[PDB]
Amino acid sequence: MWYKYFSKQSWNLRVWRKANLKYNQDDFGMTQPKYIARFGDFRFRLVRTEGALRGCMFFVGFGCFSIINYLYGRYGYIINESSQKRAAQDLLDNDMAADKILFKNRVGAPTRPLRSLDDM
Amino acid sequence: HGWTSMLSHAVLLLSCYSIIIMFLFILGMPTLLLYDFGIFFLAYLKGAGKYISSVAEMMFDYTACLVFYIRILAQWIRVVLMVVTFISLSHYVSDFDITNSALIGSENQSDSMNELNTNFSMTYYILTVLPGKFIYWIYEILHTFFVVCSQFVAFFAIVFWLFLFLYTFFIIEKHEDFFSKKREERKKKLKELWNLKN
Amino acid sequence: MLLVKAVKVLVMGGCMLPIAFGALGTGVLFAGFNVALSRNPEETESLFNNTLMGFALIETFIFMSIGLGFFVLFA
Amino acid sequence: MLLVKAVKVLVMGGCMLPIAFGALGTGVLFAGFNVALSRNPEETESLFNNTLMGFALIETFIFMSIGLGFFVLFA
Amino acid sequence: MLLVKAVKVLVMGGCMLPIAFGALGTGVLFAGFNVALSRNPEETESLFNNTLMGFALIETFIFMSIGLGFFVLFA
Amino acid sequence: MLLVKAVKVLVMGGCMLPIAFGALGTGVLFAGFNVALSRNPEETESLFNNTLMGFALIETFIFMSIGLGFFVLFA
Amino acid sequence: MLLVKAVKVLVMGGCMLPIAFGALGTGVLFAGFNVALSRNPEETESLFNNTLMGFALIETFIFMSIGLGFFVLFA
Amino acid sequence: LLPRAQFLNLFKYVTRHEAVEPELEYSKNYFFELYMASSVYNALLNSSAS
Amino acid sequence: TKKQKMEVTLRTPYKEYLANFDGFSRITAKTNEASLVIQNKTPASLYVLPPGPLKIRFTSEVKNVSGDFLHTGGWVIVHADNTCEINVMDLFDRKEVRADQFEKGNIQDLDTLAGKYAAKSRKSTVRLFTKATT
Amino acid sequence: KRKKTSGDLDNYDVLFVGANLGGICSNHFDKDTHGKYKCFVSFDQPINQIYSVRIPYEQQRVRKSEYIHFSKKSINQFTPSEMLAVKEILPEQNAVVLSSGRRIGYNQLVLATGLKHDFSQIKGFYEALEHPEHPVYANRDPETWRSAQHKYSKYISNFKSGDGYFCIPEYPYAGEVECFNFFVSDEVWKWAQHHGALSPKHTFTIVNANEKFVHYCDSADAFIKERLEKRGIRVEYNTKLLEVHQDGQKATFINTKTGEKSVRDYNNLYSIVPSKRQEFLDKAGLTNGNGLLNVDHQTLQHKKYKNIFGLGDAADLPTTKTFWAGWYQIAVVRNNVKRNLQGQTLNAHYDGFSKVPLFTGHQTLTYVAHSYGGVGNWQHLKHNNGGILAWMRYRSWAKGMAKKFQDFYNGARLGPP
Amino acid sequence: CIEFAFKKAGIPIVRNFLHSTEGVIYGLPQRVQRNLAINYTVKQYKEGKAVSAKTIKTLQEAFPSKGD
Ligand SMILES: CCCCCCCCCCCCCCCCCC(=O)OC[C@H](COP(=O)([O-])OCC(O)COP(=O)([O-])OC[C@@H](COC(=O)CCCCCCCCCCCCCCCCC)OC(=O)CCCCCCCCCCCCCCCCC)OC(=O)CCCCCCCCCCCCCCCCC
Ligand SMILES: CCCCCCCCCCCCCCCCCC(=O)OC[C@H](COP(=O)([O-])OCC(O)COP(=O)([O-])OC[C@@H](COC(=O)CCCCCCCCCCCCCCCCC)OC(=O)CCCCCCCCCCCCCCCCC)OC(=O)CCCCCCCCCCCCCCCCC
Ligand SMILES: CCCCCCCCCCCCCCCCCC(=O)OC[C@H](COP(=O)([O-])OCC(O)COP(=O)([O-])OC[C@@H](COC(=O)CCCCCCCCCCCCCCCCC)OC(=O)CCCCCCCCCCCCCCCCC)OC(=O)CCCCCCCCCCCCCCCCC
Ligand SMILES: NC(=O)c1ccc[n+]([C@@H]2O[C@H](COP(=O)([O-])OP(=O)(O)OC[C@H]3O[C@@H](n4cnc5c(N)ncnc54)[C@H](O)[C@@H]3O)[C@@H](O)[C@H]2O)c1
């Protein structure tokens, strides 16, 4: 007679795999939008819940961020080395132009940069 | 810590270890709480998402997980205040004025006893200057008591009390209620004894 | 180099801005407590327990700023 | 170059402005919660729920800026 | 060049100013929603909906500001 | 050193900002205490204690700033 | 060196900010005291004492500010 | 006449006629007396005259 | 749907003073929080007046009424159809105040939570009536 | 400055019957004449659902606030309004009697009563549409649903199995092309069969009471029937839904051609609400045949009773009864009506332009543009097979159209031109 | 205070006016004094169980309260 002493007020939830099945995922959460495409539908279809998906992407994110950070260290010069060489000579061209037009006192200090707009 | 003075070469040995024990085990309490939640731990913190993009929510979930810990670690700045405020008082007391002019029959004749010692402070020293040093003393210690007594409460009332009030709870629903009905049947079995008024 | 240092310290001063607003937000919070208390003092405990909770969150951000403050000053 | 970096670290300091308004904004929300509670303390549940929810959106903007801060500081 | 570039990243920081006012504006909105609820909690769903709606409009400005930021940062 | 010291002392001036907001928070707090006292004077002592109590939370930020002020002024 | 002295006197001016907020805080304090008196004139003397007391706390910030100013102006 | 319990639950819905000088929690119980005493006082007179 | 300019009704359980009157121009009374003023077009609202003074201005002089009274307590309702009704326990004129006749045997009270408010109110009205005579 | 005109009058010079399109014309009629005339408006329903964004609404790309609009908003403040339907119309006397009974006179009458929905044509339909769980769906939301009910968005999602029926009533009906969602459901249901969410033994057939989908455009209807077969959808013509049993999920269909009725089990039923002709327009001798107003195809003026006009859906016009078609029908009525009050001629002619999007995919569409003679413009059936071009046009209509119907009712934004 | 007198104590509004005028009944004319009078009888109704006389009218006699 254990069911005689069972309280039906525990039926407020249907817990299965640490998840309540009586959750309105159609009106709340990432699953509410019905304009999701083939990829997002197949993604939720696998996990059935946003709480489980967000949990896995939490760790998969560090994996991707820690990887692209490595590829950008190992590789990366393939696409930005030109902008670095560009800014290198550019940083020398403007420096060379500064020494030409700048007031240097008896010591090598630009004490009057506000002499004109070009000096600033 | 007085009773631990001879147990080592550092009187504060047991205290320097405990501050570390106190830090690591408080640091693991939130970590074990997320492990207890499971893979849904992010819904326990932030709730349901808003956007269909997992990359978008991934950023809002990292904040909630950071905020989850900042609520804890940011409270250790309270311990920094209690220490800094406690050290400033020790520095004022350890450096407080004590001279041969307050000693009875001093033999330290080489410590300013046989020298001409004037100053450029206010006169009526014991009526003007010396009380002011005691006035500041009372401020340093009252400011210390109010700080250490207050930061002590706020630390435990936020790290443990409030932190667990936000992420944990107790259910009002029950699954079994067989005590209520057995007590009723038991009370009818003892009806005759109660009639005698025990 | 020396300039960014002068800026690093300058930013550290800005951290005292929430320290200012936190004081104002307190006077406002405690003002509501008094009026709320004078309105219905029988329910003090509830009104009160919610007060400190709010305040805890208030100065928490204040400490948070100091964190970023020393960070940018040394990172 | 060096100045652009000096401005970047400065923009990072500006992030402590919402931190200030968040404290004031928090004191206000909890100030009304007290009064709103004293007026009708029977409904602690609903009011209290709305408090933290509102608080969430408030702090949400706080950390959003902090994220924006480190972004401009390194990008 | 770098001067205009310095102003670009500088404006990018200014976008955190509405973020501060958005935080304060949120506390005021919910503080009223709380008081508005304790007065007549019969209209939870109504008041609640009107609340989040107004909040949604606020994020429009917030996102609008950030959008203006990156735009001016690169254009 | 001397260059950074100049901005150090300038930052120390920033600590006078909470000194301003703390005053305003005080004027507002005692205002609520007075008006609230009139509505229900039966609990005067209760309100009075909470008033000064709230004020203690104001000078908190004050001393915190000055402490942080002299600190960066020398650290 | 010379600039350090210039920023010192500049900070000394910053002390006039709490002087401004203290004025507004005082007006607000007496503003509530007036309405408070009209609500319950039977206790005018009690309200009055609390009015000046709060104001005394305001001048504390004032003396605290100028004190810091004159200090940083000479230290 | 409706009882006290039914009157209060009905009176809280009052929104067209503002009640802020005395708050609604006090006004609801006060005007209930007026509603009840008015009928009683009038009934006694009619019966006493009869 | 709507009513004319206004109508006021001042009634007392033992006498009716104004079943319906339109000549009055303004009404002012003292509530618990503060003094209010009810006149034409006053929106809907309820009020409860403690034993305070009630002053009402008359465009044309009404017989037997002075326009200044001290009531012992009453209810006020401003109906939706621009109509206000004042119902007080009793009414009298200031000229019949007969001051200095207070505290004639009813000073004794009981030390309880209810007796506390009883004495509180009694003292509040005494200070009020004394001022009302001025 | 200006004072609101009076509504408690015995007669006016202009009278609008309708708020969806009859309100947009009035608000446009005043600004064209600068308020020289006093016009009255009388609608029947308080709410006007934006059916032009019905499909983005079912996709929850449009909140319920941006899809539900009151009739008062379409009407301006100066013009009075009253929610009482006309009980009868007497053109010989130039007056209109309302349900209450107050006789009102007029000089020019504009009718925008459109097609009135009649849920009673299908027994048990409304009661099943209002049930928050039953799989019976419709084209509009009942007025009993609150802001927390989103059953409309579960037609495509909750189709795990069973027999599905998309029913189309007998022409004339409202929502010819703006309510055809059998191309988005196919793409969404093609995915469900891929990962098993939708059982493989399911049946979806389009029950079209009429013989053709688009009556006044052969190019569009030929494209639809061509695309439906390419997708693999089945259709049944001359069959109209007749009854719906909410207990056993039985749908009673009837083939008007053969008069043979059948009963079919259903598990996901969608139907476009059927219309119904109003008798007060037939008793006055204004409609012709089907029940639409007998008006000129160019000037929109009624054949007889030249002082009366008609536009919207109630008008008998050889074109698609869309909303953009209404934008060009209000500019004509405000012109001609402006000329009748001044005795001038009618120089405004309606070309029969109508523009409505056809959603060819979950996030793709193509515009069905055609004039009176079914001739399409440069936009007619372009980027129909999907692509980047159709994808952008879709986002422009879903995320940028519902926010525009607020201005249309206010007046800040007028028609396209 | 009329509001707190009812909240923290079960004092009805009518009883408050009575306690209010209680201290000024003599100041008011005799016309009003005769009006402020309550005297009746309450019986718990069996043949002769109880006979209660309600004459105080200010304490927990006519208008009971929580404080009493
Ligand atoms: C570039 C530098 C690279 C550096 C190196 C990087 C190295 C990386 C290595 C690793 C690879 C990354 C791995 C990622 C996965 C990691 C795990 C994970 O995250 O989980 C899965 C995760 C799933 O994503 P999700 O968040 O769940 O999806 C969102 C929704 O749920 C989706 O909702 P939905 O499914 O319902 O519908 C989605 C979509 C509908 O989706 C579709 O319909 C598309 C489906 C089409 C399928 C077609 C198939 C074709 C067949 C294949 C080929 C056949 C071959 C044919 C024959 C060929 C013969 C040769 O609907 C929409 O309308 C979407 C919104 C509109 C689009 C917004 C895009 C904004 C981008 C702006 C950039 C503009 C640049 C233009 C430049 C163009 C020219 C260069 O995958 C990813 O996150 C992908 C990575 C995203 C990272 C973004 C970071 C960058 C942010 C933008 C930067 C902008 C550019 C800046 C540089 C510009 C320089 C010019
Ligand atoms: C320098 C280092 C710094 C880092 C320090 C980090 C240290 C932190 C230590 C934390 C503790 C780690 C220990 C984890 C224990 C896990 C044990 C376990 O496996 O139990 C499972 C357990 C989940 O089980 P459950 O929750 O009890 O119930 C599951 C339900 O019943 C299931 O219901 P359902 O069936 O509906 O769910 C569906 C499914 C959904 O799954 C999915 O989402 C699907 C994903 C997609 C899969 C790919 C699909 C591909 C499809 C291809 C299809 C192709 C077909 C094409 C067509 C073919 C045609 C033929 O869910 C699952 O089954 C997956 C759940 C298990 C995921 C495990 C994730 C944790 C991995 C951690 C890796 C780290 C390892 C190193 C640890 C280091 C420790 C020293 O895992 C957890 O609970 C994880 C809890 C984590 C909480 C701790 C978080 C700590 C955060 C640390 C970062 C702090 C940041 C802030 C720091 C601030 C400054 C200090
Ligand atoms: C027909 C007319 C005939 C008569 C006409 C002529 C009348 C006489 C005119 C006077 C002529 C000038 C007098 C020159 C001779 C002075 C000889 C002498 O022994 O002076 C030594 C004495 C010490 O100087 P020193 O030894 O040469 O050292 C040189 C430097 O000080 C060293 O520099 P430092 O910075 O290093 O020194 C620190 C500085 C520290 O800085 C300070 O000066 C401290 C100042 C803080 C207190 C200031 C407030 C005092 C008044 C408060 C009362 C206000 C009441 C009203 C409030 C209204 C608010 C609007 O000084 C001190 O520390 C002094 C400490 C010793 C005094 C403290 C203890 C005194 C005991 C008081 C108990 C009184 C109980 C009644 C007993 C009466 C009989 C004895 O000199 C003075 O203090 C001068 C006092 C001048 C009086 C000031 C006003 C007093 C008002 C009291 C009102 C209450 C009584 C009402 C009476 C009403 C009568 C009508
Ligand atoms: N997809 C659908 O099911 C659907 C349904 C209705 C409208 N619409 C859209 O609305 C557009 C224009 O709508 P419409 O103006 O042709 O008609 P309508 O649907 O907007 O209704 C006409 C207005 O007049 C009122 N009305 C009807 N009979 C009335 C009567 N006897 N008395 C008083 N008022 C009466 C109606 O309540 C309404 O306010 C259409 O082009 C169409 O796109 C679509």
Image (cartoon, coloured by chain):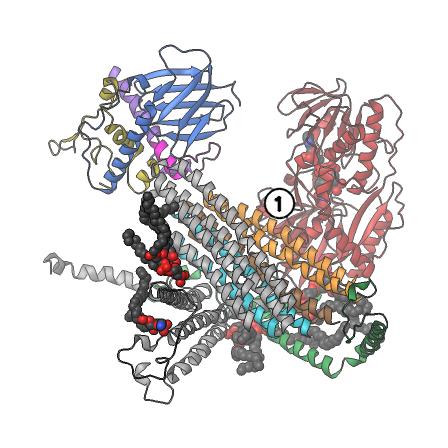
Chain colours: A green, C cyan, D brown, E orange, H purple, I blue, J red, K yellow
Does residue J194 appear in this view?
A: no
Which of the image's four quarters has the N terminus of chain D? bottom right
Q: Is residue J280 above or below residue K11?
A: above
Nearest the camera: B30 or E27?
A: E27
From the top left corner, tell me how far across and down residue K4 is, in percent: 33, 40
Give the residue displayed 35% in from the left and 81% down from the top. Answer: B114
Nearest the camera: K55 or D70?
A: D70
Does residue A53 appear in this view?
A: yes
In the visual, does D61 lie left or right of I3? Answer: right
Nearest the camera: H47 or A93?
A: A93
Marks counted in the figure total: 1
Find disc 1 in the rendering and name its residue.
Answer: J125
The chain identifier of the residue carrying mark 1 reads: J
Q: Is residue J171 above or below residue D64?
A: above
Residue B25 location, quadrant = bottom left
Q: Is residue D2 magenta?
A: no
Give the residue displayed 45% in from the left and 47% down from the top. Answer: D36
In the visual, does E26 lie left or right of A116? Answer: left
Dot 1: within a 10 Å radius of its alpha carbon, few (fewer than 14), some, or many (20 or more) residues?
many
From the top left corner, tell me how far across and down residue D68 is, in percent: 65, 65
Nearest the camera: I99 or B55?
A: I99
Q: Which residues are magenta?
A: H13-32
In the visual, does I69 lie left or right of J354? Answer: left
Task: Label 1: state its secondary structure.
Answer: helix
Query: Ligand 3 falls in which quarter?
Result: bottom left
Question: What amino acid is labelled 1 in the image?
Answer: Phe
